[PDB]
Image (cartoon, rainbow over all chains, first blue to last red; front, side):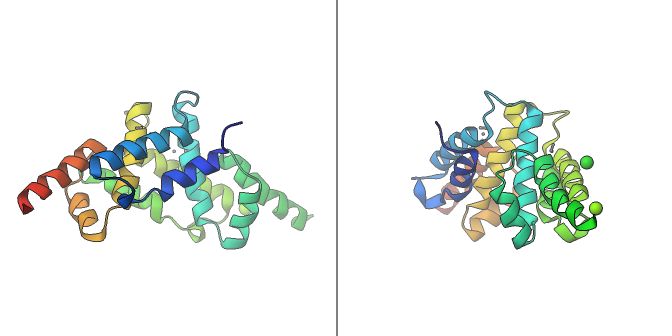
Length: 93
Length: 92
Ligand code: EMC
Ligand code: EMC
Ligand SMILES: [Cl-]
Ligand SMILES: [Mg+2]
């Protein structure tokens, strides 16, 4: 199949300004990388916004929680929260 | 354009995990700050993605160009490029 969304998201964030001959080209390449992650041909506005939120949520998690969440390959913010809440539940019981 | 979207975007990016009492509330607050920046009630899908591209383009500029472009508050990627093209021409 095609690459996992996370490969696309990383390529979008890892593209470097000196990778293209000038700003017009850089902006064109970024657009193309961003479409391949956020997939506007298949996702609604709401689904896109959810992926943008999820990315930032992962970015701000303390390291140990971040690794755990990452390993669960979440596709939205609810999935990310529930895998932390599953630990917390099992500790509170 | 307006100096305000940069405000809401920086608030979305600067929000810290310790500012919420827990993960559910953290993600809830992120959704709201995200919506304040990307304004889905007034922007199309295509317009939202231009704001995501614009943020990454400015993020990859070297330090002074980054400050220069930021201070001109471009509303999209095309506008950011023109800012750099206008500067190039004022320096040559
Ligand atoms: C649904 C996250 Hg702006
Ligand atoms: C505006 C193309 Hg991700
Ligand atoms: Cl919730
Ligand atoms: Mg709680």
